[PDB]
Image (tube, rainbow, N blue to C red; front, side):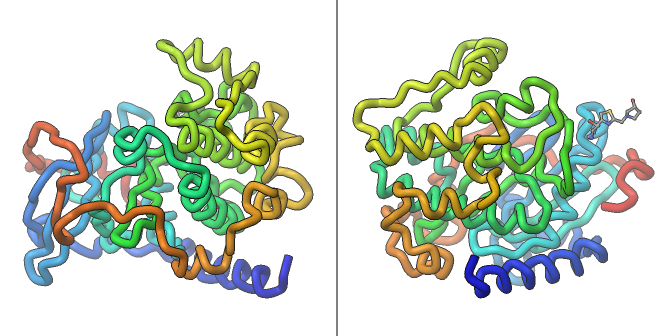
Length: 340
Ligand SMILES: O[C@@H]1CCN(Cc2nc(C3(O)CCNCC3)cs2)C1
């Protein structure tokens, strides 16, 4: 690669390792914030819009229930998420501003991106044109180049995890399955439609699973639906391990060729995992119009800007039952979460 790219990545790794080896802890508390609205909810946590009482700034606060984290075998995953987020720095990653814990919960306080999830915009418009899909895909290619050079795998790429910001660019959120991996890793995790064959088959796997998931994401952005789907997960998995993929006739020949190389069932033949690494993707014909430096510098005009009224507008997120943030009078699971 050009020495300027090599030097960029060498410094990125130096700065990551310094924060990785000495993580920040305990940098706010719950009563520093006013609760506004629930933005999302899952099996062991939720994300709430909050406002800091002294500065007036808005944030997305992820709240994880310690007891549910333990029951669902997510302890190490939640420790990975916070340790990685407090150590990374890249234009297309949502920034962690504070973290802390109390008797009941773990808290990660992230910047609030008001434009909504890419998933909502995709389903409202139907499908993105190839230039629009390519603008987003270029940001993911650069983000994975950064993460993989730090020995990090992301493991949850899908449209719900890509937020659209006030300039129309992507912010990747949700590091719940991200991990530092120097060789292979073995946990079964991720969303069925996006899993690579080697995860489904219980093999030791590597960063090539993120490049498979980028093929699924680019197909879904340009078609409007993912390439492998079915009513039951087991039927999705049969489709994935065949890798049989039919493309819409409106796909360009260059898009089909890129996708056959990202959706390659043999991980040793998959683009992103060959001798030339990410450069097989950056130099592919489907990306011939992409100015990689201009994208990184945020100098390209975006395909659209979300409609919203201000930094606290929630109109691009959906409505959930509003539940208490209860804090037990007694400490739960203190040992398991000592390092958080
Ligand atoms: O029963 C034994 C006593 C403690 N138990 C720890 C566990 N670890 C998992 C992991 O999935 C393994 C891979 N790394 C992510 C977490 C599931 S149970 C195992």
